[PDB]
Structures are given as structure tokens and as C-alpha cells.
Image: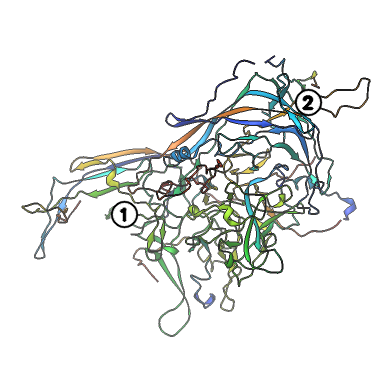
């Protein structure tokens, strides 16, 4: 009781090719449904949509949410990382938790005294076998404060199963963690544990110095030939003929290449300028989506894509990318100024543009009496010969996701971007221990429903040891970098207004340094 | 299922397109309303993975 | 022979992750709208694979 | 065989291609494919395969 | 006073021909 | 009379990197060797001149 | 599948050229030199994989000139972007070389699937 359960170890340090990091933060803990379980479907509803049907259970437990970056890296540091390395991969992960306390609450006549009940407890555990429905990879708010000095409550916990409208199937499952071992914990006593990642491809945080169509030499010509003439051109007469030619520096467009662009999914385009968009509500109808088991759901953010082509800064994919909201944003119908969009001009290097056709192809075989057929392609799969780059990550973005334990998975690279694993870090869950109120003087068959409402709190931290491939480029010309513009601004960046609320100016990318293709 | 792997009690801290036109009376004009993903609008929430490959076929009855 | 001398295979087990054969894969757009251009929307019945997909092969039978 | 082809210049228009960053470029030789089916020795893909030139060939047409 | 009196050991496990079980309850 | 191998783009995503023209791919392909004739200036002025030189003995090796 | 690859280079000579009144005498300047290098880190834009003519003579007895060299970057029409890069090999170590002195080096491939050179029976 009279001894700290540890020190506040929160720093960023660089010893060379590795980087260690940790962030201490203070949390709180509220009970839920008075330690009771629940069932959820079109109940505390919305009305009727096989597409908005669900089935799950709200449990009296809580969990941790730190699958983002602005939670482990202060801005500046992140920057440091960006301008010097090409890629990185997180290897080690530690976890500490301490300085627990317990508070009770008596609300008498509106007058409520809050003292502590040092003798109460809690219990937490981990799932190293991943038998519990994974909850992360959904970017649910309530992540560790992007900021360090603020404090927060731990979001309750609830999962779902295979459902059929407002009813469940037989195969639907139902779990209860009260079935799992858990290091019990009383005040003053500490708890920590440790895990280590496994092998993963360093997410390449850089752009390309060339595009798939300009990888050849401009001073020469391919020693091959290609079709350049279907008809004669020598006067005023048209006849069937065949003119073949090589590929020159002036006809680069036709030169035979060796590789192929990446996969694609056409999407409707939209403008940041309100008046340039058609006047029709197509948010849900003209939207790109897939059909599964009758429930039609959107396809966001969809595959890896390019936001727009050159100078189309006015447009972006309908639901092809990420979006962020400056601090102080609410739940619905907010405008474009309370948000921030993601620019993906960095991939025009190799991947197609969402609002663009993949390309054209033919539908028939012509003859002297048959016209040359030509169709379009807005849907595209992959073939041998393609190469692409997954979605880039953002500081205010997600970090990794749980690879579905299945028999078939392909280039499991998540769509929101990040890292996947067959055995991801674990989920840690905690709850306030139940403590009943004054029970009757005689017996009563039924269980109890009266308890002392209370809550507990404390501070925690996490260590992350990563790997990084420092740059070796000998580009002579000075590359681009990330910096806060040097002009004068009333409110600094990543500062806190005269009120203490901490907000970010813009979202941040990583594909800044240009490495050769 | 691939569309129900998130938590029902919370919302994505991201936003998505929810309005193309204005809706406040008897007038239609170009506008943009963005919103987060809630437990009531799960259908629109941004997921992270994608369904499998396919080949359309004609249906038939028993 | 008729349907009664035979037995068919039920595959309701994959609606979990894979599409349904007699169903569209989903829709996409064919154009870029403006105040004078209507929102284009086509269908997809043929689909290849991309980074981000996952599925489960056909189940086996005794 | 010259006479069996339609009489229209589609070398660049009716050609198979992809769109990238606004620059539309041909798709040659494209993925792995089959030149033709049996006895179609008269035809081949518009831009689906390789081509060579005997010694003494020049640049165009 | 400032130390838990133990951990919450409640599981079901099968090592073969034997089965261990425990249930914690308040 | 064809190509032999090609440089696999150093990226995060590549699939069955088998080149299209055919051949072999590598994350670390053979290298590129480059040479040039060394520059040798002509008769320079008798006094100084800030600017660099542009007059050399044209030669080849 | 090709595993090993060696490279030798020798018997260098240097010629100069004086074009006086159309009368040009070509002799040698045995004291001049050149310098070459290699990129084992692939920091220079790769130029091959484009099948550009000027390969070693398909024939052995003929002789040829070495094609000049030029690369490209991310562009926007007739203008370049900021991220466009610009390199200069004069920034790389290079075994200098004078006549009579030789130069060679060696590299070895890595694992690769044997390109199957055969057809199918079904």
C-alpha cells in the first residue's frame, strides 16, 4: 500500500537501427450493465435492413484500444523516422500495468462522497490462443489519448456472431471469459506480461522514382516490332495493308513493356467543390459495393488505389480512401471543413486511379465486313506480371489487424494498411470485481442484483522495439521532406489552444522519401 | 462474417461520405455531409479485408 | 435420372466469407459525374483477386 | 493476309490498353497468352506477342 | 492488505484420460 | 533472339514476378556496369578565367 | 537456371583525333584513361529489361559501339515534379583504368524457378 508499483517509463530513444518506445497514460474503469450480460439485434435498433442486421452480446467487461500510431509516437519523432528510413517492422512488445486504486460511490440525497475501498479488486487476462472474437482492426475510437497528459475511460466490450435478421442460427456461438484464468489483482499489487512479434515484410515507406511505362532508355529503340499500320497511306486510296515498326523515343507509348500495373475497382468520383457534383443522392445507391448472403455492404476503403491523377485535386474516390476529423467533431452530417481527406497521388507511379477505367479490350474479331469491337474494363483481377504497393499508413491511422484463421489467404496485407499476423498481439480485458450489497436476513433462492456501484483507475504503458532499413540512395538532388511551414500562424501546430484541447492540423503520410524503383 | 468483425458499442474514428445534396425543407442543392460509422450504420463502416473471388452462374430450383 | 435418385450439396457454410454463385459480386461505376452528367453504375459478375482477399476452399465429402 | 482485315485504322484506337495517371499506354505484350487456336495460322493477337526483324530492317512502316 | 490473495484460476482442460476443472465465483 | 531477365521493382507487393516478355526476375539482379572516356582539356588560356572549360581533345577508346 | 556469372574486361587502348583541313591523323595517347564501376546496391535507375538494341553482336566476329546512357523520372508533361530525382554517378567509386591495366569482377545469382522449356502432353 505504501509503495509505488513502479516508475513512469515513457520515452523515445534511438540506439541505431532499432527504436524503442513507450507511452504512459492514465485510465479509468466503469462497471457495466451492473455486471450483467446482454443480447443484441434489431433491439435498441434502427428498423429493417438485412444489411443493418446484427447479433451480439454486451459483456460487463472492458478492454484496451491502442491500435494506432499517434499513441506511441509524438509527432516530431515520427517525422524523424520518416525522413531517414525506408522501411520498418515492429519486433518486440512489452506491457506494464500498475498503481491500481478502487473507488466506491454513495449517492445520498444528491450528496455523494467518494472515498476508496482499498480492499476491493479486479482481474485481467490475455488470449494467447485467440479463442475470443477479435475486436481490433476496426479502428474504434477510444484509443489511447493521441495526447499523453489527458486521461480516458476504457470502452466496454461486445462481439457478434452469424445472424439471420433479428434471429440467430443454431451454429451461432456464445462465449463467456469468466471461463478464463486471470491474474487477480488487488491494490498495490502490479501486473505485466510480454510478447514478441514474428516475421513480417517491412512496410515500404517511400515513393517511386519512375512509373511502369518509363523504365526504358530514351536514347534507343527496342529491337522488336509492333503493329503500326492497318491501311495504306499514300494518296487518296484505302486498302488493306500491314506496316510494322520498331519502338522509338518518339513512340514510347507503344513500346512493349515487361510488367503490368496493379489490380483495381472502379468507383464514382466526387468533388471537394460542392457545385461540380451531380445533384442526386447516390451516396448509397450509386456507391460501389459487394453482395454477400443477401446483405449488400459497401466496399470501403476497398483495394489499394490512387486518389486522382495529376491536377485533379478537386476530386477523390467516392469511398476509396480514408478521412479524418479535427478535434471537436460529432457523429453525423458534419461538413467537409470539420474533416480531412487523404491524398494518394504517390501511387500513380504503379497503381491505377479509382475513378478511372482499368483499360480497354476487344469483344470481337473483325473481317472486311465486321467492325473492330472495343469494350471497357472497370473490374480487374490479377495475373502473373503485376506489382503494386499497399495503402500507405497514417499517423492517426491503424497499425495491424488479425488475419482470419482460414485455409486461404492471399497477400494478407490489410486494406486500411498496416501489418497482419497469423498470431497477432493479444487482447487484454479487465473489469471491476462485483461486490454485493446488504443481503437479506433469511434465505432467497434467487441470485443478487444489488451492489455497491464503484469504479477503479490507474496508469499503464507499453514498450515497442522495432526494426528499420535506413536509406542508401545516392540521388544527388535534394529530396522532399516533411516540415511545418515557416510562415507565421496564430495557433501553433500540434499545440493546444488557450483551452488545452489538443488538435492536429493535417493528417500525416509516410511515403515522403523517394527511393529508386 | 467479413462485415461483422467490429465492435457494436463504438464507432470508427474515421468518416465517410453520407450526403450529396441538402435536406432542409423544399430545396435541392449541391452539398457534402460527412459522418462517422456508428452501430446503426454498420453497413457503411470501412472494413479492412475483402471477400473472395467469384464466377456468376445461373440459378435453378429443386 | 431424376432428382430423387440423387443428392445435392449444401454450401451455406461459406456465406461467412465467400460470395454466392447465383449472385452479383457487387457494383461499380462507369463514369465520372458533373452537374450535367448522371451517376454511372454497372454490375460485376466476373471477378479476379486483389491484395486483401481471403476465402476457404470447397469442403470435402466422405 | 492483308485483305481479310477490316479497312479501318484501329492500330491505336481499337487497341487494348490501360489507363494510368491520365497517360493511356498500350498493353504489350500483355500477360501470357495463346497466339491462336488450331488452323488459324492466318491470325495472331493485335499486340499480344513478340515480333522480330531480319537483318537490314529500318525504323518505321 | 496491498496484495491479492491469489489469482483467478478457472478453466477446463483435457490432458488425455484425465480432466481438470475449476470455477471461480464471487 | 529474346531478353533474358529483368529487374523486379523493389516494392512491397509483387506477385508471381515472372516477367511478361518472359525470362527471370530477381530482387537483386546482376549489376549494371558503366564506362566513359576520361575528360582531357585542351590548351587553356595564359591568364585566369572564372568559368570552367569546354575545349577538349576529342578522342575514343 | 543460370547460377554463376563472371565478367572480364581487357586490352584497353586510347585514340585521339586531330581534324586538320579534313586531313585527320589518328594515333594513340597511351597515357589517357577511363573509369568504370558497378552498382551492387542498385541505386541507379535500371536500364535493362527494355530490350534496347545494341546488344552484344549476335555474331562474334563483328564489333560495336556502346550505346549512350539516359534515364527518366516522375514527370508532368513538359515539366517535372518536386519529388523528381536527379543522379550523377560521378558520385561513385570507380576502378580507374589506364592502358595495359585490366579489370574484372564477379557475381553469382540466387535461387530461381527453372524456366520450364517444354510443352504438355494433355
Q: Which chain carries label 2?
A: A
Position of A375 compared to D28: left or right?
A: right
Residue A514: give x, y in percent of width and height: 42, 47
> Which corner quadrant of the image does residue A333 belong to?
bottom right
Give the answer, above or below, for where C61 lies relative to A129. Answer: below
Q: Mark 1 points at which residue?
A: G69
Question: Which residue shows up at 40% across the image and 81% down it?
Answer: A234
How many dots with numbers? 2
Return the residue found at the far bottom: A236
Q: Which chain carries label 1?
A: G
Q: Is mark 1 on a helix, strand or loop?
A: loop
Residue A503: give x, y in percent of width and height: 54, 44
Position of A38 compared to A15: left or right?
A: right
Quarter of the N terminus of chain A within the rendering: top right
> Which corner quadrant of the image does residue A100 belong to?
top right
Residue A295: give x, y in percent of width and height: 75, 53
Position of G96 compared to A499: left or right?
A: left
Q: Which of labels 2 and 1 is toward the front?
A: 2
Residue G91: give x, y in percent of width and height: 28, 44
Position of A382 compared to G1: left or right?
A: right
A426 or A214: which is nearer to us?
A426
Q: For label 2, count other residues whose C-alpha is less than 10 Å away and answer few (under 14), some (14-19) or many (20+).
A: some
Q: Name the residue under label 2.
A: A434
Q: Real-space Cα distance between discs 2 and 1?
A: 77 Å
Amino acid at each position: 500500500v505504501g509503495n509505488s508499483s513502479g516508475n513512469w517509463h515513457c520515452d523515445s530513444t534511438w540506439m541505431g537501427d532499432r527504436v524503442i518506445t513507450t507511452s504512459t497514460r492514465t485510465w479509468a474503469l466503469p462497471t457495466y450493465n451492473n455486471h450483467l450480460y446482454k443480447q443484441i439485434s434489431n433491439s435498441t435498433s434502427g428498423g429493417s435492413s438485412n444489411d443493418n442486421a446484427y447479433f451480439g452480446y454486451s459483456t460487463p467487461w472492458g478492454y484496451f484500444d491502442f491500435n494506432r500510431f499517434h499513441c506511441h509516437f509524438s509527432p516530431r519523432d515520427w517525422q524523424r523516422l520518416i525522413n531517414n528510413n525506408w522501411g520498418f517492422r515492429p519486433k518486440r512488445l512489452s506491457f506494464k500495468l500498475f498503481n491500481i486504486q478502487v473507488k466506491e460511490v454513495t449517492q445520498n440525497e444528491g450528496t455523494k462522497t467518494i472515498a476508496n475501498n482499498l480492499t476491493s479488486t479486479i482481474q485481467v487476462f490475455t488470449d494467447s490462443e485467440y479463442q475470443l472474437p477479435y475486436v481490433l482492426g476496426s479502428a474504434h475510437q477510444g484509443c489511447l489519448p493521441p495526447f499523453p497528459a489527458d486521461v480516458f475511460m476504457i470502452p466496454q466490450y461486445g462481439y457478434l456472431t452469424l445472424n439471420n435478421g433479428s434471429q440467430a442460427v443454431g451454429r451461432s456461438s456464445f462465449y463467456c471469459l469468466e471461463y478464463f484464468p486471470s491474474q487477480m489483482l488487488r491494490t498495490g499489487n502490479n501486473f505485466q506480461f510480454t510478447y514478441t512479434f514474428e516475421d513480417v515484410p517491412f512496410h515500404s515507406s517511400y515513393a517511386h522514382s519512375q512509373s511502369l511505362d518509363r523504365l526504358m532508355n530514351p536514347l534507343i529503340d527496342q529491337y522488336l516490332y509492333y503493329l503500326s499500320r492497318t491501311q495504306t497511306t499514300g494518296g487518296t486510296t484505302n486498302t488493306q495493308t500491314l506496316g510494322f515498326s520498331q519502338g522509338g523515343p518518339n513512340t514510347m507509348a507503344n513500346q512493349a513493356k515487361n510488367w503490368l500495373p496493379g489490380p483495381c475497382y472502379r468507383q464514382q468520383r466526387v468533388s471537394k467543390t460542392s457545385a461540380d457534383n451531380n445533384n442526386s443522392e447516390y451516396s448509397w445507391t450509386g456507391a460501389t459495393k459487394y453482395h454477400l448472403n443477401g446483405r449488400d455492404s459497401l466496399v470501403n476503403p476497398g483495394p489499394a488505389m490512387a486518389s486522382h491523377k495529376d491536377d485533379e485535386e478537386k476530386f477523390f474516390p467516392q469511398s476509396g480512401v480514408l478521412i479524418f476529423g479535427k478535434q471537436g467533431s460529432e457523429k453525423t452530417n458534419v461538413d467537409i471543413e470539420k474533416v480531412m481527406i487523404t491524398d494518394e497521388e504517390e501511387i500513380r507511379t504503379t497503381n491505377p486511379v479509382a475513378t478511372e477505367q482499368y483499360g480497354s479490350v476487344s469483344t470481337n474479331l473483325q473481317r472486311g465486313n465486321r467492325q473492330a469491337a472495343t469494350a471497357d474494363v472497370n473490374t480487374q483481377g490479377v495475373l502473373p506480371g503485376m506489382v503494386w504497393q499497399d495503402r500507405d499508413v497514417y499517423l492517426q491511422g491503424p497499425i495491424w489487424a488479425k488475419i482470419p484463421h482460414t485455409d486461404g489467404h492471399f497477400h494478407p496485407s490489410p486494406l486500411m494498411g498496416g501489418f497482419g499476423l497469423k498470431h497477432p498481439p493479444p487482447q487484454i480485458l479487465i473489469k471491476n470485481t462485483p461486490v454485493p450489497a446488504d443481503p437479506p436476513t433469511t434465505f432467497n433462492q434467487s441470485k443478487l442484483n444489488s451492489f455497491i456501484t464503484q469504479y477503479s483507475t490507474g496508469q499503464v504503458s507499453v514498450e515497442i522495439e522495432w526494426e528499420l532499413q535506413k536509406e542508401n540512395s545516392k540521388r544527388w538532388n535534394p529530396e522532399i521532406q516533411y516540415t511545418s511551414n515557416y510562415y507565421k500562424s496564430t495557433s501553433v501546430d500540434f499545440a493546444v489552444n488557450t483551452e488545452g484541447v489538443y488538435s492536429e492540423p493535417r493528417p500525416i503520410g509516410t511515403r515522403y522519401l523517394t527511393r529508386n524503383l
